[PDB]
Length: 256
Ligand SMILES: [Zn+2]
Image (tube, rainbow, N blue to C red; front, side, top):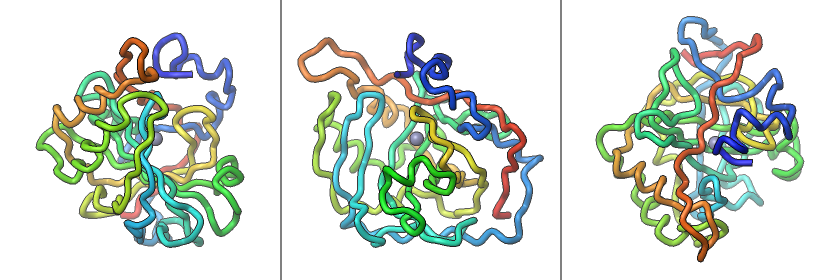
């Protein structure tokens, strides 16, 4: 599967019928229809920089993975009653610098999107197992607005020089992803899914109200990564964002 048109979002259902599921992500957040839940608690992230482990080119994107054998780095609060263990952060972007986020707000597509994913360590034993359960995953989505360069992205950008092609991995340590999050962590939340195959509807989304910046040349760097394996002709990672899916009667709750 991919993002091109032969194997892209509009073709995924042919292989993953859940693509047409009732809790698909991303979604358009219509700020006027959001429900303020007074039961929501502020989200509390507590990550240990020593759990940062590797950066890897997965072809369609790059992942920054973390050690997930303990509760050193967790997400708590929000709509949760238990702790979610951090396992990874990655991004989404588009072919253009101004339209590449997954989630949209009031129909407005942002330049890129940051996803911080965690799995339900309390109810399940492994990411593998939790990945398909309704309460399995918790993902923080942060909208990125093209503008001023974001200096907090530099270690990630620098690391990309070592994983130019698919399957390349490089150690990526001592990084606390909470440094990528906005100032305020007011959020929107809804039950949804993974935004690409397997498309499991196992995610509890936390979309930060506040966006963060990125510059044009910072995004050009992501698109400079290669989807091919070393040695083959160059095939740029031009985009990896999935179009918004019907809400299908879900409610987006707000922290405020
Ligand atoms: Zn993602």
